Length: 45
Length: 89
Image (cartoon, rainbow over all chains, first blue to last red; front, side, top):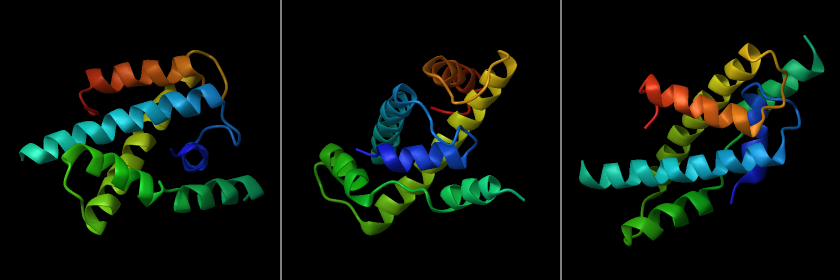
Protein backbone atom coordinates (compact mmCIF):
# COMPACT_ATOMS: atom_id res chain seq x y z
CA UNK A 1 0.00 0.00 0.00
CA UNK A 2 2.73 2.52 0.94
CA UNK A 3 6.13 1.00 1.65
CA UNK A 4 8.43 3.31 -0.14
CA UNK A 5 6.85 6.53 1.11
CA UNK A 6 6.93 4.98 4.52
CA UNK A 7 10.65 4.16 4.16
CA UNK A 8 11.64 7.73 3.19
CA UNK A 9 9.30 8.91 5.96
CA UNK A 10 10.99 6.80 8.60
CA UNK A 11 14.38 8.03 7.30
CA UNK A 12 13.20 11.61 7.31
CA UNK A 13 12.27 11.11 10.96
CA UNK A 14 15.57 9.72 12.15
CA UNK A 15 15.78 6.03 11.32
CA UNK A 16 18.66 4.43 9.40
CA UNK A 17 18.94 5.52 5.77
CA UNK A 18 17.82 2.01 4.92
CA UNK A 19 15.35 0.64 7.51
CA UNK A 20 14.45 -3.03 8.04
CA UNK A 21 11.54 -4.48 6.03
CA UNK A 22 9.91 -6.18 9.00
CA UNK A 23 9.76 -2.72 10.65
CA UNK A 24 8.34 -0.95 7.60
CA UNK A 25 5.42 -3.38 7.53
CA UNK A 26 4.63 -3.27 11.22
CA UNK A 27 4.47 0.49 10.71
CA UNK A 28 2.14 0.05 7.75
CA UNK A 29 -0.29 -2.01 9.79
CA UNK A 30 -0.20 0.66 12.52
CA UNK A 31 -0.85 3.45 10.03
CA UNK A 32 -3.78 1.48 8.61
CA UNK A 33 -5.11 0.75 12.11
CA UNK A 34 -4.68 4.49 12.76
CA UNK A 35 -6.56 5.84 9.76
CA UNK A 36 -9.41 3.37 10.41
CA UNK A 37 -9.73 4.66 13.97
CA UNK A 38 -9.77 8.34 12.97
CA UNK A 39 -12.29 7.62 10.25
CA UNK A 40 -14.65 5.79 12.59
CA UNK A 41 -14.25 8.51 15.22
CA UNK A 42 -14.72 11.30 12.68
CA UNK A 43 -17.90 9.57 11.39
CA UNK A 44 -19.38 10.09 14.85
CA UNK A 45 -18.33 13.67 15.60
CA UNK B 1 26.51 20.04 7.05
CA UNK B 2 26.63 16.52 5.66
CA UNK B 3 25.13 15.14 2.47
CA UNK B 4 23.11 13.00 4.88
CA UNK B 5 21.60 15.79 6.94
CA UNK B 6 20.55 17.37 3.65
CA UNK B 7 19.18 14.12 2.28
CA UNK B 8 17.50 13.19 5.52
CA UNK B 9 15.72 16.58 5.43
CA UNK B 10 14.66 16.32 1.79
CA UNK B 11 13.03 12.96 2.53
CA UNK B 12 11.31 14.41 5.57
CA UNK B 13 10.20 17.42 3.57
CA UNK B 14 8.56 15.46 0.78
CA UNK B 15 7.72 12.04 2.16
CA UNK B 16 3.99 11.50 1.81
CA UNK B 17 1.43 8.78 1.39
CA UNK B 18 -0.13 8.14 -2.04
CA UNK B 19 -3.58 9.77 -2.15
CA UNK B 20 -5.09 6.84 -4.05
CA UNK B 21 -4.61 4.33 -1.21
CA UNK B 22 -5.61 6.78 1.53
CA UNK B 23 -8.82 7.51 -0.35
CA UNK B 24 -9.68 3.85 -1.15
CA UNK B 25 -8.98 2.96 2.48
CA UNK B 26 -11.31 5.65 3.78
CA UNK B 27 -14.10 5.29 1.23
CA UNK B 28 -14.04 1.55 1.75
CA UNK B 29 -15.13 2.33 5.33
CA UNK B 30 -17.68 5.12 4.90
CA UNK B 31 -19.19 3.49 1.84
CA UNK B 32 -19.73 7.02 0.52
CA UNK B 33 -16.92 8.61 -1.50
CA UNK B 34 -14.81 11.37 0.08
CA UNK B 35 -13.25 14.73 -0.78
CA UNK B 36 -9.82 15.85 -1.92
CA UNK B 37 -9.44 17.76 1.37
CA UNK B 38 -10.33 14.79 3.59
CA UNK B 39 -7.61 12.69 1.90
CA UNK B 40 -4.95 15.41 2.31
CA UNK B 41 -5.93 16.11 5.90
CA UNK B 42 -5.86 12.39 6.70
CA UNK B 43 -2.39 12.16 5.08
CA UNK B 44 -1.07 15.05 7.12
CA UNK B 45 -2.36 13.57 10.39
CA UNK B 46 -0.99 10.13 9.55
CA UNK B 47 2.41 11.56 8.75
CA UNK B 48 2.49 13.15 12.21
CA UNK B 49 1.47 9.79 13.74
CA UNK B 50 4.27 8.06 11.86
CA UNK B 51 6.54 10.81 13.11
CA UNK B 52 5.62 10.26 16.73
CA UNK B 53 6.09 6.49 16.52
CA UNK B 54 9.53 6.63 14.84
CA UNK B 55 10.64 9.41 17.18
CA UNK B 56 9.46 7.38 20.19
CA UNK B 57 10.98 4.10 18.95
CA UNK B 58 14.29 5.85 18.23
CA UNK B 59 14.26 6.75 21.91
CA UNK B 60 13.68 3.13 23.03
CA UNK B 61 16.42 1.85 20.70
CA UNK B 62 18.69 4.55 22.17
CA UNK B 63 17.89 3.60 25.81
CA UNK B 64 18.23 -0.17 25.27
CA UNK B 65 21.79 0.56 24.26
CA UNK B 66 21.18 -0.27 20.62
CA UNK B 67 21.70 1.47 17.27
CA UNK B 68 19.36 2.04 14.32
CA UNK B 69 17.86 0.76 11.99
CA UNK B 70 14.74 0.51 14.13
CA UNK B 71 13.73 -3.10 14.83
CA UNK B 72 10.17 -4.45 15.28
CA UNK B 73 10.68 -4.72 19.04
CA UNK B 74 11.32 -0.96 19.06
CA UNK B 75 8.11 -0.06 17.24
CA UNK B 76 5.86 -2.13 19.40
CA UNK B 77 7.51 -0.99 22.62
CA UNK B 78 7.15 2.61 21.45
CA UNK B 79 3.49 2.04 20.76
CA UNK B 80 2.96 0.82 24.32
CA UNK B 81 4.59 3.94 25.79
CA UNK B 82 2.66 6.30 23.54
CA UNK B 83 -0.59 4.62 24.65
CA UNK B 84 0.41 4.99 28.30
CA UNK B 85 1.19 8.68 27.82
CA UNK B 86 -2.18 8.58 26.10
CA UNK B 87 -0.78 10.57 23.18
CA UNK B 88 -1.77 8.16 20.41
CA UNK B 89 -5.15 6.45 20.08
